[PDB]
Length: 167
Ligand SMILES: Nc1nc2c(ncn2[C@@H]2O[C@H](COP(=O)(O)OP(=O)(O)O)[C@@H](O)[C@H]2O)c(=O)[nH]1
Ligand SMILES: [Mg+2]
Image 1 (cartoon, rainbow, N blue to C red):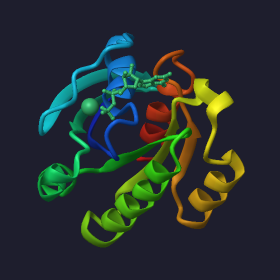
Image 2: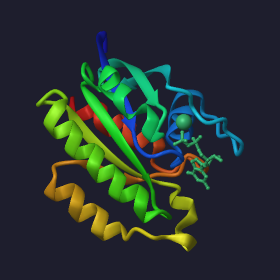
Image 3: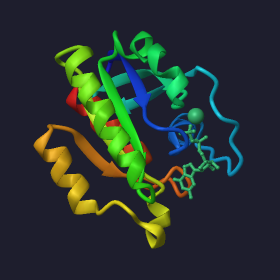
Image 4: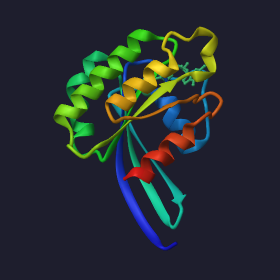
């Protein structure tokens, strides 16, 4: 197809849960066991083929530390979609993700598409958040949920493409 679409996506979530790794896997097909903590935010782009459309993603990878919380609106205000990330081995990060979802529902665009990534799914032997519980939470809050692994690539391209399909 010759159609072209571009949308703004922001990633939010506690640090560290693998936010930068998720983006790096999607954008560069890389995974770094040793990642420097993000300072403020990082910007990345990726262009893909979705049926008959060429879709370009403008992605804001936010630093998740609480001291950066006040800067989050700079990145989500104009966002068409968000991926709120948690780590499936860390229940506290899952609770933090629900608070990010609440903030987006109240302060971001009313039509923003919100995805929820239960990351580090390759560490299921250390699971702290039940898949079905997360799925139910996502269903009840109209969120696009998938467990992902930046380390193995599991569902990484899939969650980004699913968001694009719904925009
Ligand atoms: N096992 C595993 N480690 C991961 C995964 N995603 C990220 N990590 C690791 O967890 C750490 C934090 O990741 P990073 O992307 O910097 O987290 P951020 O602080 O949320 O941006 C790094 O040591 C990564 O290699 C994943 O899916 N599986
Ligand atoms: Mg980061």
